[PDB]
Image: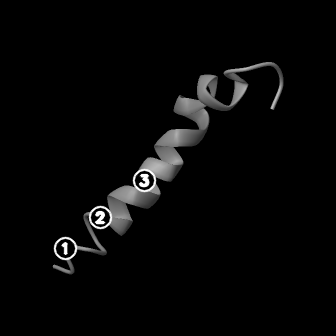
């Protein structure tokens, strides 16, 4: 952390990974295609 949004400011250098993770957990997993 840092002050308040530091964990969100890295949305690009951090969330897109959780998103790539979800894109694989929702597009790959969940759907199972």
Q: Is residue 16 positioned above or below 4 on the image?
A: below
Q: Nearer the viewer, mark 3 or mark 2?
A: 2
Q: Which residue is mark 3?
A: 20
| Image-based side of 12 in relation to 1, left or right | left
**Which numbered dot is residue 31?**
1
- Locate the C terminus and report the quarter of the image it occupies: bottom left
Rate crowding at label 3 as few (under 14), some (14 to 19) or many (20 or more) other CA atoms within 10 Å. Answer: few
Q: CA distance from mark 2 to mark 1?
A: 6 Å
Q: CA distance from mark 3 to mark 2?
A: 10 Å
Number of numbered discs visible in the structure rendering: 3
Marks 2 & 1, CB-CB < 8 Å contact: yes
Location of residue 28 in the rendering, given as x and y in whole percent from the top left corner: 28, 71
Q: Quadrant of the N terminus?
A: top right
Q: Residue at x 25, y 64 (%)?
A: 27
* Comes first in the chain, label 2 or label 1: 2
Rate crowding at label 1 as few (under 14), some (14 to 19) or many (20 or more) other CA atoms within 10 Å.
Answer: few
Seen in the picture, residue 33 relative to 5 is either above or below; the reply is: below
């Amino acid at each position: 952390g840092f002050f308040a949004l530091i964990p969100k400011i890295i949305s690009s250098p951090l969330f897109k990974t959780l998103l790539s993770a979800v894109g694989s957990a929702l597009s790959s997993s969940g759907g199972q295609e």
